[PDB]
Amino acid sequence: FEGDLKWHHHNITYWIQNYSEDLPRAVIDDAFARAFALWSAVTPLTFTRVYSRDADIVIQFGVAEHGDGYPFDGKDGLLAHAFPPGPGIQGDAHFDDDELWSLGKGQGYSLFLVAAHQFGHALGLDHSSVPEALMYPMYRFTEGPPLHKDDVNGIRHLY
Ligand SMILES: O=C(O)[C@@H](Cc1c[nH]c2ccccc12)NS(=O)(=O)c1ccc(-c2ccc(I)cc2)cc1
Ligand SMILES: [Ca+2]
Ligand SMILES: [Ca+2]
Ligand SMILES: [Ca+2]
Ligand SMILES: [Ca+2]
Ligand SMILES: [Cl-]
Ligand SMILES: [Cl-]
Ligand SMILES: [Cl-]
Ligand SMILES: [Cl-]
Ligand SMILES: [Zn+2]
Ligand SMILES: [Zn+2]
C-alpha cells in the first residue's frame, strides 16, 4: 500500500458507497467530512462528496474478503486500508466493519481519526516516524488537532 504517485488535480471527489452498522449515516457522513477538512485546511486541495463510481476516493465498509486481495481479519488487527493515488481502485478507502466504530473517548476506534489517517494514504502520504503524527502506523486515541507539523509538511510537500 505504498505508492509513488500523486493526484494531478486538487479538486478531489469522494463517494460514500455504504455504511457501518455502528453509527447513524449522518454521523458517518460528518466524520468523513471532518476528516477531509483536516487536509483541505492546510493545502489548496478541496473535497467534494459525489454519488458516482467516477469519484476519486470511493469509501466503503466491508468484512473479510471485499474485492481486493487484502481481506479484513475481523475483530481487531487490520482496521482499514487505502490505496495510494491513481485510477480505478487506487485512492479508495476501505474500513473493516467487524471493528467497533465510534468517536471520541471510549471503547471502539474513532472513525474520524482512522478516516483522516486513511485519507492521508489516499492522498499519497506514507507512514510517519513521529509518534504524535496522524500518519503514525500505530492507532492511539488522543484529544487535540490530529495534524502534527510532520503531517502538514508531508502533505504540503505533495500539493
Ligand atoms: O496503516 C494502515 O493504513 C493499515 C493498512 C496497512 C498495513 N500495513 C501497512 C503498511 C503501509 C501502509 C498501510 C498499511 N494498517 S492498520 O492496522 O489498519 C492501521 C490503520 C490506521 C492507523 C492509525 C489511525 C489513526 C492514527 I491518530 C494513527 C494510526 C493505525 C493502524
Ligand atoms: Ca485549503
Ligand atoms: Ca479511486
Ligand atoms: Ca480487523
Ligand atoms: Ca462495526
Ligand atoms: Cl449501507
Ligand atoms: Cl473536527
Ligand atoms: Cl474522535
Ligand atoms: Cl488538525
Ligand atoms: Zn480493501
Ligand atoms: Zn497507515
Image: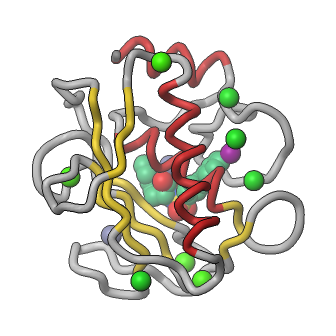
- Where does the image place residue 10, in percent across and percent down from the top left? 27, 24
Residue at 53 percent of width and 17 percent of height: 42
Measured as percent of width and height from the top left, residue 74 is found at 53, 86
Give the colour scheme of this rendering: secondary structure
Give the image quarter of residue 51.
Answer: bottom left
Q: Position of residue 89 (x, y in %)?
A: 18, 59
Q: Vertically, is 6 above or below 1? A: above
Give the vertical position of 99 relative to 6 (above or below). Answer: below
Q: Which residue is rendered at x = 16% and y = 42% of the image?
A: 86
Rendering quadrant holding ligand 4: bottom right
* Residue 157 falls left or right of residue 89: right
Identify the residue at image location x=11%, y=47%: 87
- Note whether 46 is above or below 50 in the view shown: above
Q: Is residue 124 left or right of residue 75?
A: left
Q: From the top left corner, tell me how far across and down residue 16 is, in percent.
A: 37, 64
Q: Residue at x 82, y 58 (%)?
A: 104
Left or right? Give the position of 68 relative to 155: left
The residue closer to the viewer here, 22 or 76, is 22
Residue 94: quarter of image: bottom left
Report the quarter where the C terminus lies. top left
Answer above or below: position of 125 versus 82. above
Callout count: 0
Q: Nearer the viewer, residue 32 or 92?
A: 32
Q: Nearer the viewer, residue 155 or 19?
A: 19
